[PDB]
Length: 49
Length: 49
Image (cartoon, rainbow over all chains, first blue to last red):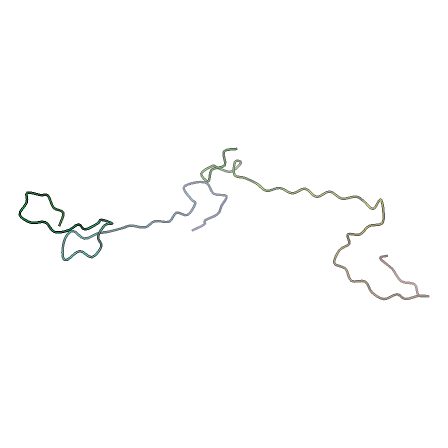
């Protein structure tokens, strides 16, 4: 490449990172920043296991 | 000013310094990196006093 500060856009260097994920293939090990609550039972509730 | 990294040439900021100086109108004090030598006498030489 010929990266020079004089060159306009379309030639200035750019940094690129691509992120790829799995889709529920095993016990997931990279979760989100959520707060696990207690464990209720015998009640009509909605869960996020 | 509207300095943005996407701006083309002719709009990116430039740093400028101008140097002015008197042409020996008094005993000068700002010399260069030259080294003073010893003094000789009674011999035809050239000097930079």
